[PDB]
Amino acid sequence: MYGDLGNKLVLEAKRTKQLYARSNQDVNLPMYHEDIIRNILKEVSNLRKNTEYLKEQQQLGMLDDKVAKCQYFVTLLCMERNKRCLLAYQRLRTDILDSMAWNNNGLDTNNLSHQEQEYLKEYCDLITDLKSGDLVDIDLSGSLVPPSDVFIDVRVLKDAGEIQTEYGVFNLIKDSQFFVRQSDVERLIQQGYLQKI
Amino acid sequence: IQPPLLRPLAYRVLSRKYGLSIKSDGLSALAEFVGTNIGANWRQGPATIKFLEQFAAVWKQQERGLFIDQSGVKEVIQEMKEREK
Amino acid sequence: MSLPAHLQQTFSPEEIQFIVENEPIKIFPRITTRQKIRHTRWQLITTDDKALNNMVAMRSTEVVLWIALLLKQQSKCSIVAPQWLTTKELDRKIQYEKTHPDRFSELPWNWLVLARILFNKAKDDFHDPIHELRGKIQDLREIRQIKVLKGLKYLNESHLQLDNLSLLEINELRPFITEIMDKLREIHTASLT
Amino acid sequence: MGYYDIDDVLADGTEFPCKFQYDIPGLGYLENNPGRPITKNTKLSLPLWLARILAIVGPVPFVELLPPDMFSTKVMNAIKTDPVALDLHSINSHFFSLAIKWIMLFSEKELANVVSELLLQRAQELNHHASSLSITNIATSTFLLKLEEMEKEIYKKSHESYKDTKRWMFKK
Amino acid sequence: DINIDDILAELDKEVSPQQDFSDLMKSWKNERCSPELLPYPHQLMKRLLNRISMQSQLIENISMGFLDNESKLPLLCMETELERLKFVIRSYIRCRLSKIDKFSLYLRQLNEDENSLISLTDLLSKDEIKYHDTHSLIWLKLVNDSILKYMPEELQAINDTEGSVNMIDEPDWNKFVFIHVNGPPDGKWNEDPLLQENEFGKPCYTVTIPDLKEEVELTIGSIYVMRYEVIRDLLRDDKVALI
């Protein structure tokens, strides 16, 4: 039926939600289900044409009070179910995009829709703007892990080369260890260049 | 001009703003740009912030402090400021 | 989203450890931060600076547990062992739990986390051997776990009371107990006319 | 059970047997016959989202839902025997939500009590499994296969919490 | 014998930023635990922010002096304290923004509803209100251009309650949440009318769950699990702090 396509889209949304919950690190999100979404939209257009025909039949007056009322109610319920399924899937994908923007953009374009990519860019701009102004003193993009360790030994996961610090330039030559405060090396760890001393 | 004096300033204004690496040579180039004004150019600090924002918008590349691209971006931002004037 | 899905319902063990660190603890300084009438200062905005600035060598003082452990990383600080964290007190709590299977021994809510953190760092400060305290802590944890199993067998949708249960135990039990009680309440509400 | 909840949407999309209380021409699409009018006493399984509304409204309600095999007294007896041994997932992945919806549509105190007892026993087994942590097992695999998708999500959350706690305890 | 404790006490009787930090910690814990968004304390948040700014300026001045006694351990202590305070503030603000996005529809409904006791600006900060308004507008534009153009105008409303499940999403008042009875905010137990003697000489606060119409007493200094709606009265009274 018309709601079966929306049910399939919601099933894909639940599958992606379970996958993202299973993997702590953010995987490249599944490609947007444009085919199922377009099928649901075509079904919605067909239901709208059917509702227009039912309204024309009501203008004709034949069983307009009861039969046409029930038919229009059923068609409207189908449209509402399809819209709810599409909204749920889009909201889940957009929440995944917001989580990704908080994870990386604060410090897989083919998978996203073009509107979704524009929305993710707008979300990154909003995050940068929220940090840019009031409450700029604390890096809102900074890690939410509590500062358990003031100092921690750090060495390069990758040979990125010279790196900036509060008052120093540190070479990231391969397998080069350091002893520095965790706060200064938090950004470098977010870059992935240095891991666990 | 006064690259050591601008070094903490550039480091904050760039790395804290965007997470972008600032090479010491790029900080020195920004220092020469600042010294292009005979006196201290405090407005040029906001100009450098705007230049970094434009570079992030266009190039969108980490390690912008290499200054091979940042010098051309500085020329572009200076032309934009001239058009704004 | 801003909040991780696991964090939506319960605090992480690291967050509970951060709270326990926010708690204070006694320690013995080895630096005369207090200056004689005859210098850098803490000037802490969230905690007292006078105690840190008045610390003198081998003069017992209390400070927030995180700062206490930070100083203990240096040789200057030696944390004072909690009195309940003694072999006799642990044996008393174990005997109380044995005599009262229903009633948990009046351990602090952060007893488990504090004992684990002290074993990680303050094991040297313990006059009693650390192994005996660890064994007593394991025995108390097993007794409390058996009591928790009995209580879960005796769950009720209306409410529950856990007086002396550890804060870490409460945090661990929050998801399962909350979900089960919410499902039971939903079933009862659907049964209600 | 949110409007955007995909699990709730699927449970609503599940069909349940029903018997028509009215004869409506032009509703043959539900009958799957293009031009056949609906007839009274006709028996047809309908999606829960539509079947529940038809049972609620209609005065004589437009349709009356027939009792599903998942709600059958034989399944109830199997549950009373052994809540854990029964394959609630095989019966329905949203079996508990469907039971709650059926209780809301028709208040049944005994059904609620049986469902609560089954949920309690299965939750005790799931808690034992989640407490069991690595330092896939066949027993846990069969238990999960019996367990519905919602119960499996709850078990995954609890087991992940226990595993994270154990890892944080055993690692610095 | 004669009791002179009152005389001894009378003879003995002859804004703390640390307390503000403790209050912020309690408020952030209650915000994380409570499904409902707590009212925004503007004065306390602003005072904490001003203290953070002054501390950062002082640390920068000390850094300049060092670059020019000389012990950086206190400077590291101040830096760690500032980092912890900023982390707590950012976590509370992020949780508040999460609640705002979760109940954007209900917050628009409350702003539209003059009958609502709390003004949206009263509940939120100024930045929070601007963020909620702009985010709701952007989401409405996206959803409208996506589906509402094809949707019939009678069903095009995004926040309408006409659907069987209302599209507006509100906090679950009845949701269960753990709580520890803080006791009366005043030191005197008798001074609090809610505080009352219970069996075995234990002060307690009577509470009721509307669904079951059951009444229970919560002992002071004790932990309990209860629906957030009934708990909200004692939470506004500050008699109990959410775990």
Image: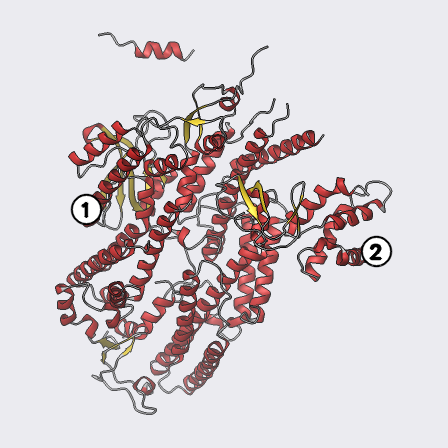
Check if mark 1's residue and mark 2's residue have beta carbons within 8 Å: no
- Asked whether E151 or C68 is in front, the reply is C68
Q: Residue furthest top?
A: E2
> Going by the image, does C94 lie left or right of E114?
left
* Residue C164 visible in image: no
* Residue that carries the numbered disc 1 in the rendered image: C150
- Classify mark 1: helix, strand or loop: helix
The chain letter for the residue carrying disc 2 is B
Q: Quadrant of residue D36?
A: bottom left
* Residue that carries the numbered disc 2 in the rendered image: B82
Q: Measured from the top left, where is residue E123 in percent x and y?
A: 48, 45
**Which residue does the image show at 35% across and 49% down from the upper left?**
D166
Q: Looking at the picture, does residue E84 appear above or below residue D113?
A: above
User: Which amino acid type is marked by label 1?
Assistant: Lys
- Classify mark 2: helix, strand or loop: helix
- Asked whether D40 or B42 is in front, the reply is B42
* Residue B2 visible in image: yes
> Going by the image, does B51 lie left or right of E149?
right
**Which residue does the image show at 47% across and 23% down from the upper left?**
C29
Q: Measured from the top left, where is residue E230 in percent x and y?
A: 31, 44
The chain letter for the residue carrying disc 1 is C
Closer to the eye: label 1 or 2: 1
Q: Looking at the picture, does residue A113 appear above or below residue E40?
A: below
**Cα–Cα span, label 1 and label 2:** 78 Å
Q: Residue furthest bottom?
A: D35
Q: Measured from the top left, where is residue C22 in percent x and y?
A: 44, 34
Q: Measured from the top left, where is residue D71 in percent x and y?
A: 19, 70
Q: Residues within 10 Å of mark 1 (few under 14, many from 20)?
A: few
Q: Quadrant of residue E232?
A: top left
User: Which amino acid type is marked by label 2?
Assistant: Glu
